[PDB]
Image (cartoon, rainbow, N blue to C red; front, side, top):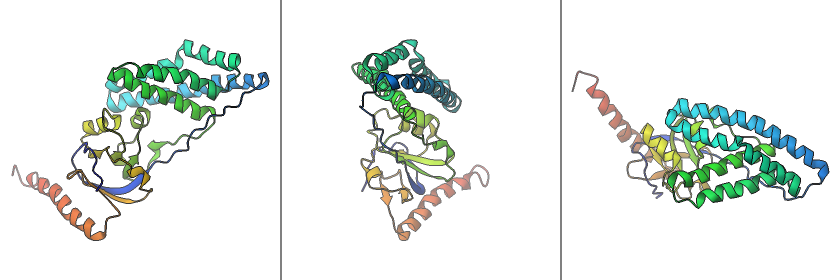
Length: 259
């Protein structure tokens, strides 16, 4: 009874992989000139590893999807390295006595909102992607661990409310059998990679992420635009025969000669 937008046709079986993240909380406490020096080291030093980690992902986007996607990530890194934005963030900490996480959010607050004022798909989408650059920085400033999605060792379905271009660029396509998320479906980066790879996919899940837990057994039919949650063995057996019968029918052509 879950009808999504159907991004690609096909049928797949696997466990539901739910991605859970800890919410990021900003501290609104004002520090004294005694701890301001520490903010500069964490901010200045944070950019040191952040630039290195993000820089590695840029190559993955170019070697995984080609230079077509590398150009989008290359521009985002320039913003982080802009000598102008760094000086402003530093001034807010010393001028307004704000923490590095709090001061950084102020700059990002206008960079993201400013891009939303433009009515271009690239500039507008850049607004969401730019917010991601600041969101990751916040997780680094507080020392929050990052989930490494490229370390998956079990073949299962990927389920998430939404994926950011950075997470998709470093995603492992060999261990994921499909993508099912709760994205509106308008220019969704996840759906775009799916169409290029022709793998089955869906995005209009609505609220499945709030109704499924990790390890749930799900069947993606990508045919009638419906997903089954907690299906009985009788249902699985029926789809296993008809679904596999389709794949076996195509193998008969290449088994003999040309028929």
